[PDB]
Picture 1 (cartoon, helix red, strand yellow):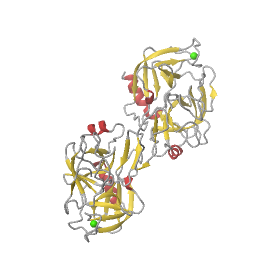
Picture 2 (cartoon, chains in turn red, blue, cyan):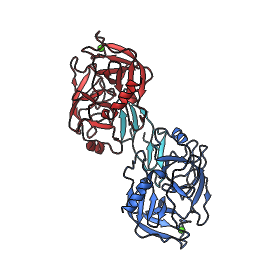
Picture 3 (cartoon, helix red, strand yellow):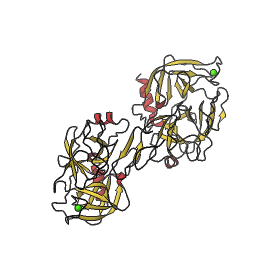
Picture 4 (cartoon, helix red, strand yellow):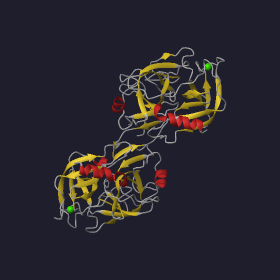
Length: 223
Length: 223
Length: 55
Ligand SMILES: [Ca+2]
Ligand SMILES: [Ca+2]
């Protein structure tokens, strides 16, 4: 996260890390058996690491569970990143405690202005790279689809929201993909793509989760 | 047109050439006052040259009329080329005679297999460039959306059809953009984009005109 | 450099490079989108009226 803070213990319990050797993306726990991430984070073989904080040392409070099902949104487009959302069903339910917990799907969409908390173990340098052991957090508002489109033209579809600052300096970055953008206690975004990190006039584009709630419902109940 | 034939006199009367100094794209006459072309051919200032056969010499049977209105499809995307269609309203109606005539919009869509005639004054070499004086014609079938998608993945939307040959050798090429793909006497396609020209496995992608008939109707009637 | 390039059939052609590359697009590229994975899947959204490099 470029320019955010160390999150503090048991602050972000739905944060999930996707591992296949090492952290390559993050995700959110949405119920004891299903994690939501981004479709471009797909691998066959993903190990979900739950209750993580320092991902570099084992602190005995973590749960590592293999993914049994990895399902990318059917209409996901690898070139335009539209419908960038993926559901992972865990081969065993995570035991929910303080360190491990569920985010809620949206009662509705966020309105331009709402502040949110973005979180991840991704890079912390817009120019260069440092990869933090500890989970980084960032407060940022949802931008207007109008700002979002003017910032990235011909690219922002109606399933993508920009969250961040037009003046740069604070943003999600590589390693954060798939992570949560939680606003008012509801998961409104998934970190997806962007032009570089924390650049001026380039805010993060996140998958608009309010558009997919019934798909999520439908897949969880049908699998 | 790579590998097609010289068209023969008064064979393709709806063919239009868009000029702004020189031929840069083509189009079709759809009624005496409105030409349909492709949205990525947009210039402010276009001169429509009608009844053209040899575009290099004046043969006294041509009509040159300025465009008064150039309207690109509202949802046209310059990056993915979706909704690549544009309507030009002529500052005076073309006088319709044998050399100048109207194509019909689709009663329905073409079905994979239908033979069509593509036409234009664009390049004739897949490797290199020759630009013909005389209008070139090419007979080619509409491919299945399934072949089309497998040939260009993540790129073919539901407003694009592939017409041509999976073998290669015959296709449209630069200079033909905007031109007609007429099947059964109905304008089913507009030439748009492709990887290279007449390449193996890379047939041309054209704008699917049956999807826009009511848009064409209301723009013509509302302007 | 570019392997896949999609040009329109206009004089001049409007060209795009379709390659998703590893962590990078190129150094000649002014419109590079990357996913925020580790590594990033990056694509150069540049348009050039003719089709070669970006490098
Ligand atoms: Ca740990
Ligand atoms: Ca002439």
